[PDB]
Amino acid sequence: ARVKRALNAQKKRRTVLKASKGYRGQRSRLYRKAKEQQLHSLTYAYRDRRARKGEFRKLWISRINAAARANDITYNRLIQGLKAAGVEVDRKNLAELAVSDPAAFTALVDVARAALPEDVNAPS
Amino acid sequence: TYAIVKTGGKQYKVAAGDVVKVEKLDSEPGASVSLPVALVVDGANVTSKADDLAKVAVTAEVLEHTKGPKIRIHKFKNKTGYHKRQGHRQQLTVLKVTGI
Amino acid sequence: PTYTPKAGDTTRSWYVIDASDVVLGRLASAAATLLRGKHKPTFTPNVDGGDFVIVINADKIAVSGDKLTKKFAYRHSGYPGGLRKRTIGELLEKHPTRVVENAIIGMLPHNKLGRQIQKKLKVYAGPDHPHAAQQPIPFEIKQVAQ
Amino acid sequence: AVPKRRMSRANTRSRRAQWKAEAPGLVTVSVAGQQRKVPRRLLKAARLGLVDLD
RNA sequence: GGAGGGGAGUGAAAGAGUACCUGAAACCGUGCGCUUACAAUCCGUCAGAGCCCUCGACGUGUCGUGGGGUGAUGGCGUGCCU
RNA sequence: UCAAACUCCGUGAUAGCUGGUUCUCCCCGAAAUGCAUUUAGGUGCAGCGUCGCAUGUUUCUUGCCGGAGGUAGAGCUACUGG
RNA sequence: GGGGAUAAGCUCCGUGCGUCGAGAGGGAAACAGCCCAGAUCGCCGGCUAAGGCCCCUAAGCGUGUGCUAAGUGGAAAAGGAU
RNA sequence: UUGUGCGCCGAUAAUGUAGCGGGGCUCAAGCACACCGCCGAAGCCGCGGCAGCCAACGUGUUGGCUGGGUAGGGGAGCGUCCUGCAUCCGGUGAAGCCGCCGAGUGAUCGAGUGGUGGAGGGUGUGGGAGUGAGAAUGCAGGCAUGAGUAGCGAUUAGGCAAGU
């Protein structure tokens, strides 16, 4: 029985072309270029999903450092004091507190200062 | 007043009435759950001592079990002919906070 | 989710920094930090949330070593043999502002946003500035001890 | 010399947009009573009835 | 002038008019929404301001376990096959 | 069209050479070494992969014990040479 | 270790040596073979390796004792130098 | 004089700074030795989803290890056509095509719907394949870039008035 290849190819062509909407130039019209761009786009998405956590952590660290320096304390000393004090709030909510509730961040800075050792450079 | 609640290896800043998506929990919709607290900020004074945090908990009701966005994975390497298609829909629960 | 500035959230303040007896690198780094907006808790690399910076006493900048007569500021016109070199000494004696401008500009991103941030830096060789109507806040370069 | 590459849609359309015709300027005229538009270059000719006007 | 077309008719249908069943893709237009003339872009991906549309609730506009379109701006990023 | 014309047929000539060979996922996963070759860009066997059957730690690492070298070093009226 | 002029980003052998080949991620500005480390998928959680903490660029214009005047740092020899 | 830690000339090519990645730094942001923090990967941990092997007890749950991968080996499946058998849908509108809203671990799916269309299709279980193209300076048809660009084919030459 002779079989025509229309439907089987048209299915995947429709899916690939629909997935490539919004692209510029040939990448949104022609199936081959759209498929190449789909490969690249999905690889980029997979890599960026992994890198997004680090990107957001870097942004939170920047905001926390800015807020802490506004309270006359460095980010690293503040983190060490917070770890010593036992407060387990992560950097995401720390940055949220810094942006939204400066009083809570000031209180946390105070408790971190309290928890820090007397001479940070001592061999202890 | 609001508190930072730990659940599913993560922490969320919530108050009374907030709806927050949370990693899957073995609870039927409409039930109630109690979760630990990483920090309580009531008005001005901030509760941060470990034992004070242990003495308090956040009670929330499970709204529904849902699924996250569909994620398409197509691993690929040039000059190789190696492809690997894969999909994933993370399971989630929707929690409405009742009080602290 | 993480906070993101909206249209009306950004606010600017004016800082005036005196450059009399200041190491050029230190002053330029402080000015770049102020312009970038890195000192605000609401910082976001997407947005230009920096602050307007005024620099006076530009001609009084301090340059250590022998960099006054051995450091060159190069520029090429594009024509053959169009390279021009001037030491920091003649550049300061001729265009006192340009030294601080180049120093600060070299320290901030070379993106389009960096070009936009450059619009918020005004330097003056004299001891006074015409921006008194904005009532700038004096700024002192301090170090947070750890 | 031959083109090394196929021109993209943007460049082709941008250069193609410069091939256009300008609209001639028309002024009115009164011939045989009825008013009609005639280019100012042909004003005198129309007034002397040297231009066929449909 | 014709070609062609607009009414009027025949037809169940003229989105069946002897260029005629169904009418895809490439390619070429028209209208609307967003964006673009200080900008070095394997042209995408992750964040993302703004504008427009849409689904609910409460008032007269403002949020939400919302969804869409376009996306200024930042990070990353050396087409496919042999 | 000529260092042996053109057409059909043998004919779907033959090329250790070149190019191409189309849907998906799960598990394991190499080699570029030896011998031989009218042999070196090919191939046969061996080595390494996988599947099934059989056999069970026989594999591997560490400690201890029993063994043979003639390397590094060193040495020379202990030999032979410079 | 041999050949070559112990010159080659030269060539030929040995190595329960490594990596790439067949290997993503971080670092060395970029950079198959170097360094850290072997990616089952998701997270807007945490601790670290190599490498780093003045700005670009995340984190120290960190603390203590000394040296450097050469921008040495941020290329190189015989040799010369109160 | 003796050795040391740093330095100094030696030092030196042809597009443009060019032998810190850039700015800049000796008020070290340089070097040596000590000390204290932090950043830092798809590494490890936390929560959740899947799969392979094995073990335990059960009449499929739990638990432990494992899950980069070309040549290649094995296993399991998606889609298309024609058919035996059994059922279901269809001029109250099948196929085909264009969308919306969704779904699956993948090939993909929608007896969910909106438009167009006008006569055949779906499902289960078997049987057989001309059964899946992105590339062979691949073939046929249609159409783009170059581009409204080159050219409009000699060395004689056309003009005016009238007419159709």
Image: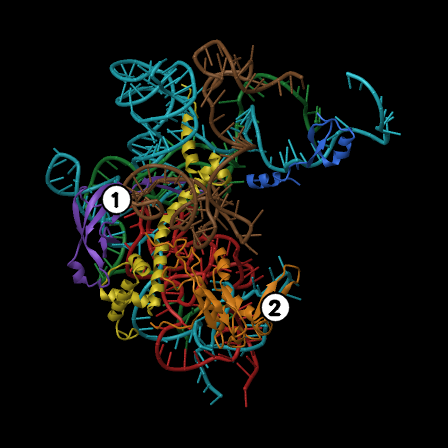
Chain colours: A yellow, B purple, C orange, D blue, E brown, F green, G red, H cyan
Between A98 and E79, which is closer to the camera in this rendering?
A98
The numbered dot on residue A44 is: none
Residue H142 percent coordinates (x, y): 56, 26
The numbered dot on residue C85 is: 2
Residue H44 percent coordinates (x, y): 27, 54
Between D30 and C72, which is closer to the camera in this rendering?
D30
Q: Is residue B80 visible?
A: no
Mark 1 lies on a secondary structure that is: strand
Residue drawn at the location 32% of the way across and 61% of the way down: A98
The tally of labels here is: 2
The chain under label 2 reads: C
Residue A49, placed above or below residue H111: below
Between E13 and B20, which is closer to the camera in this rendering?
E13
What residue is disc 1 on? B92
**Badge 2 amino acid:** Lys
Judged from this view, the residue extending furthest toward the front is: D33
Residue B5 percent coordinates (x, y): 22, 54
Between F69 and A108, which is closer to the camera in this rendering?
A108
**Badge 1 amino acid:** Leu
Horizontal side of residue H22 vs B9, given as left or right: right
Mark 2 lies on a secondary structure that is: strand
Separation (CA) of disc 1 from disc 2: 64 Å
Residue drawn at the location 57% of the way across and 68% of the way down: C73
Residue D31, placed above or below residue F78: above
The quarter of the rendered structure image containing the C terminus of chain A is bottom left
Is disc 2 surrounded by few (<14), some (14 to 19) or many (20+) residues within 10 Å?
Answer: few
Is disc 1 surrounded by few (<14), some (14 to 19) or many (20+) residues within 10 Å?
Answer: some
Residue B82 percent coordinates (x, y): 40, 40
Whether label 1 touches label 2, CB < 8 Å: no
The chain under label 1 reads: B
Horizontal side of residue A34 vs D36, given as left or right: left
Q: Are marks 1 and 2 on the same chain?
A: no
